[PDB]
Length: 374
Length: 8
Ligand code: NA
Ligand code: NA
Ligand SMILES: [Zn+2]
Image (cartoon, rainbow over all chains, first blue to last red; front, top):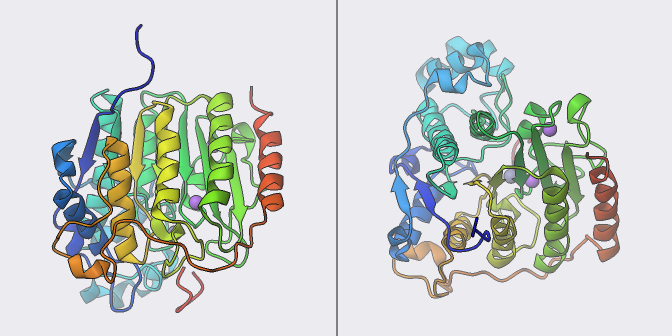
């Protein structure tokens, strides 16, 4: 009864050393090597001494079919680069072969990515940790019976379905620059999962996430979307993130939180057009962490891999409440972080097309929808 | 997703 919701949190961290060897193909922006860069960087910072590190299991087809269809999972187990010709029609109906190519060990990559998220949720359900971290997860675009946006198996939906075994209401927050369409779609008609996505909107992948998309049926008003423009910075992002999340916590009152920390919302991303720094990005982890709820932190987007390693290393230290110096320690990828070799980055001179009046107007309309909750 | 290729 003496608890006040403070103190350092117990953090469990999931990582498989084989994740960095999976290769999407020549010229493909998604590079699972960024996860190994992140792991090696936080190891050289000494963060392994403050958290428990687990190697996730390979999620089975049964675990994946808790959401995905049997036909789509069977296709993922069978498709390989040496038999693509025989599956020419199946590759098209499941949206595999372009943005989501076939590569060696594709199904194993999905198992390692998904295994970390479901094992994190199990660890949270058993009340054996405060936070669970899986940077290989967060693949928020995967649909029930098709791939999308470099994502094949939606580890988030499976991890949330695992949390729903013991938690009445689960909150999902998506700070990836892209709309969390796969997660929102899976829980669009239920009030047991509330999805909140902040993203660039307007002539941008995936094309969903309009302000007026608020859910359907029993899930109406349980889907929140904050459409943004190019060039948003730390001050403008933090001006709306904390008050929006605070009101969601007050109205919805979840018992568990899932935070997708897509790094492609950082300044200088290969595919992103935002202007956030690592501190402004990590500020979102600080806000969610204050509420002292079972929190599952996941990865996601991020295609300037040197900044992805920076972002997820610092956000792990933030989860551990460990201050780390800005001078990067030596690591196996020290040359990737030139020419400064610092941990934190600086924003660009790009224009912030999100005026302060625009941010205040979108926030006010979201507050109207949040008033419609019991 | 990728502006360099396709529609995603
Ligand atoms: Na998002
Ligand atoms: Na919902
Ligand atoms: Zn993204």
